[PDB]
Image 1 (cartoon, rainbow over the protein chains, first blue to last red):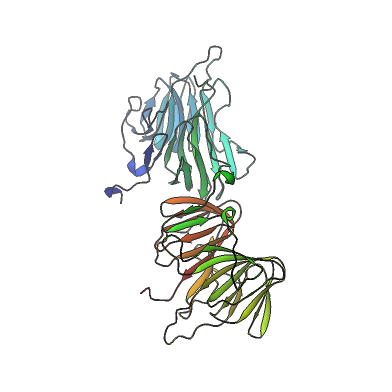
Image 2: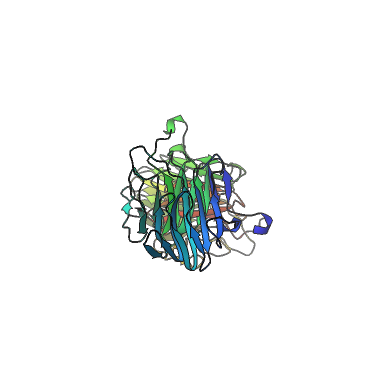
Length: 245
Length: 245
């Protein structure tokens, strides 16, 4: 019933549930030839300080650096990431963190989809910005969230003060759920990678599946429960290590 | 925190979630020495056509027949049922269907808790009222609901046109859920026996656990999703086999 206005999407002051049928393809100067679905922009509800979008890259397309930090996570296909002198071919669940300004190129070796977080860097007087960082979600042997072995967390980026943010994945066995509703000053940006369940944000519960994007404003009560026969997995962004003032 | 008005209970025109901390003990003529918690009565919101309550029987307590049909289901303890010329001890998950008027006595061998469904009997012309019937929830190896082996339904009373109603159990594996939201004329008397999860009634989602009672009004959209590590299981009541007019 999409053509009569029905959707699972919703927009609120401090959160938004963005589902695939509502997607709108636009474009970005640094991503010539690719289709861009910009899910979270600084202009959502009460405010956001980053952007999350997925780049649908046709085989052969090239994308170069922007003025911001760039975290690219390959959802499908194969993407060659060429930095200085060295270049690697990324496949499903491989990712790269590129410092703001780092000259580089992304080439789609085959039709691909890449999840991207872009954020400006908040320097710290005596700290040097982190260099390029590569990684694979699956090689990472996460930790039981808060002792729970049915909720595996995997920090994809070094948990160090030099970093501006963090990107991690949360995997829930069927029936598993966050220990409690979280309420913290860090805002979230998420993409449902695998599975389905009910996500609680403020007073409402939302049915969500792989493919959905969620914006969680600062201090937004948030909880999740995984349903179905498969494990749920979602990619998560959250600003970190900087004084809120 | 209940002393400042906090509870997971909620009352509505077509549905209600009733939690253990809100229970009020009362008494019934046929249940001398026992405490009765009348959960659902014909006066709930828009109306009910039966009564659901639990009896907390102290060892030694004896209860006799009422003028209505009585379906007793043992939650804990042991209860002797003396009907016809025989007597049987009932323990956890043992139940008995007693025709309206049938003389009988329920004696508690030990402190017991009994879930009871009572209601008048609607006679059809060429249909003789059914006789006493015994069973045990676990004996009954149910059937996969919609062909889903993680959703086992167990009919506790024979599914014949002679019966005025039906009692059954719905069991869910940690990640299971009803395949679709249900909407039907027949009302519901629900008692959570095992597990926990989220019950959607109309437009809201309610977190519930073993112990919780739920009243679903006619045509009340309903759905359930099981969470946690254990299976969920709930006792269900619903009138059947009679023309609504």
